Length: 48
Length: 165
Image (spheres, rainbow over the protein chains, first blue to last red):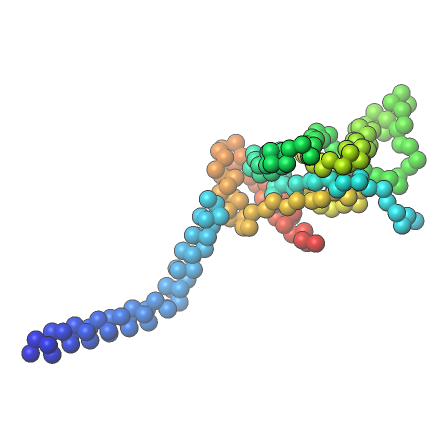
């Protein structure tokens, strides 16, 4: 009972959440925000 | 009637171009770093000379002798072209001594300004990769540079628009 309903279910939840997060990261808005952050970091390095 | 041969100094002079207008703080430190480095590492074989006056008025096919004497009271005799013309050959004599010489000219800010003359110098380009970094670098100096920041962008962008060849 414990093995099937508490560890297997936790594994399923972790897998589904990881897949959802991976799909969410590659969305257009998140990609644009990350590009902005990377460009700002390059600017800060060159400024330093 | 361009002659096949031109007279140039024996050792190529070195000129540093401002990433932006010379005589301003940011550029001034940009070239003083190189000047101190060449002086310190390469002492005993390199001479440093400063040209306070202009150097862009070096012409060879204008006239036989414009303003040969200072007592002519001509428009060109009492003008600044005489001193600039006298500045030309001292680079030649320093080059004839085999010692490398640089030019600390505060007027030339573009390679084309000093390309058709008989100096034929080595031009060193110090530039920031992006104007975004340059704007904040200018901002870091203080409120004094905020006034000339506006005209200081164009001296950078026009210069970087120049072809790299």
